[PDB]
Image (cartoon, rainbow over all chains, first blue to last red; front, side, top):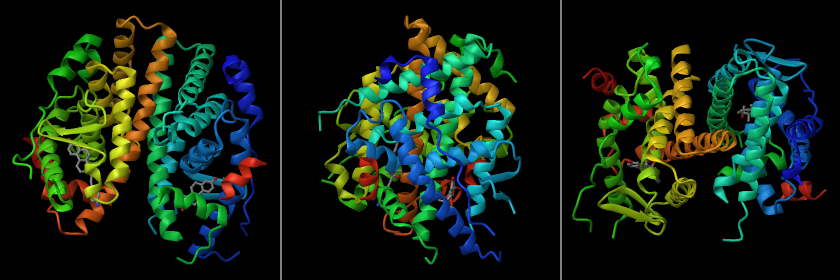
Length: 229
Length: 232
Length: 9
Length: 9
Ligand SMILES: C[C@]12CC[C@@H]3c4ccc(O)cc4CC[C@H]3[C@@H]1CC[C@@]2(O)C#Cc1ccc(N)cc1
C-alpha cells in the first residue's frame, strides 16, 4: 500500500498524521526535581500520541507487532527530541518543550540542552521545512531499530519504504529549485543530523536510567527504559 | 582551504592513499578469557589510534582546522572510526569479526566478556549490511572521513563545506558504477543512515570502556584513557 | 507490556 | 594531553 503512494501522497499522509503539541503543567516554585517531573510527565503523554502517529506512518502497520514494538522502543526518544528541536526552531537559544514551557540554557542536563539547542540552530540555518521534518521523523522511526532485528525477515520492506521517503525528500528539494548537486548535498546534511540525534538519545537514556532516584516515572516510560538497558 | 579544489577522483585517490595499515594482534593465542581477550582488543585499539591520528591529518581539509577542533573531532569519532574499519575488513568473513588478520572472532567467542555479545551482533549486522549493499572501497573511505568531520561538528562552515564535497564524491562514485539518478540518492541515503547505527554502537561501546576502567582488571593505555575521559 | 496493548488499539 | 603531541608530530 505504501509502495503506491506518490511523493505528494507521501507528504500529505505524513502531514495529516502529525500529533498535536501538548501542554505542560508548568506554573509556581520550581525544584530541579519538579522541573524534571514536568518533562517526564509531558514525555509520557506525548508517547501515547506518538504510538498512534506511528500507525499512520505508511508501511508501519504492515509490520509484525513484535517489530512495531521494537522500532518504537528504540526510536521513541529520538522522535521526542526531533519534535522538540523542530518546534524550538523559531526560538533561538530556547527549548520549547511546550507552548507554556520555554526553557533557556540557564546537573549534567546542560549537556543535553546545549546539544538540542545546536540541533535547533542547525535546522534554522538550513531553513528546514515542515514537509522535510515529517520525512526525517518517519525515517528515524523506521531506521533506528532496523539493525537490531530468524530468517522470515522481510526487513527489505522497511528499506523499500525508506527508499520511498528518500525519493520524497529529493522530490521536495527539486520543487524548491535546487540543482541535482544541491539536492544530494541537502539530503546528506539532513541525514547526518540523525547521527547527532541518535547521540543525544543515547546520552538521554543514560540520564533516564539514573532518574529511575526520586523523580517519578510512568509505567509506560519505565518499559521504554528497560528496552535500552 | 585546499580540499575544496580537488576533483572527485583526486579526493578518492587522496583518501585511498591515506588508508592506515591493517595491524596485527599479539600472537600465540592460547581459548580466551575475559581479561585476556579484552587485553588483546585494547592493545590493538591503542596502536590503531596512533595510525588513525596520522590518517586524519591526511584527510583533505582536516589540517586546515584549528588544533582544538582537530582534537575535538578525533575525541568524538575515534571509536566510530575503529568500528567502521573493523566492519569493513570483516565484510568477506560473514559471521566473524576480523579485528586483526590473526584475531578473527565469532559471536560465540564474544560471550567470554559479559555484554559483548550485544556489541558483537551489532557489529556483525553492520558488516552483513555492507556486504549486502556491495560496499566498495572508494565508498568506504568517504564514509570514514565523513564520520571524522560530522561526529563532532555539532558540539564550522569549512567542515560542512568539506562534507558537501565528500558527498559529491560519493555521488560521483555511484554515477561511475552506472547507477541511475534514483539509485544514486537512494544508495547515498542507505549508506548515511548506517552511520546512525555506527554512532549507536560507539555510544554503547563507550559505556563498556568506562565500566572497564572502573574495573582496573584489564589495563588501558593513557592515550586510550584520555579519549575516554573526553566523553565523560 | 503497555506498548503492545497500546499498539493493539 | 597525548592527543596534542601526536597531532603535531
Ligand atoms: C572498544 C571495544 C574493544 C576494542 C574493539 C576494536 C579494536 C580494534 C579495532 O580496529 C576496532 C575495534 C572496534 C570494536 C572495539 C570494541 C567494542 C567493544 C569495546 O568498546 C569494549 C568493551 C568492553 C565490553 C564489555 C566489557 N565488560 C568491558 C569492555
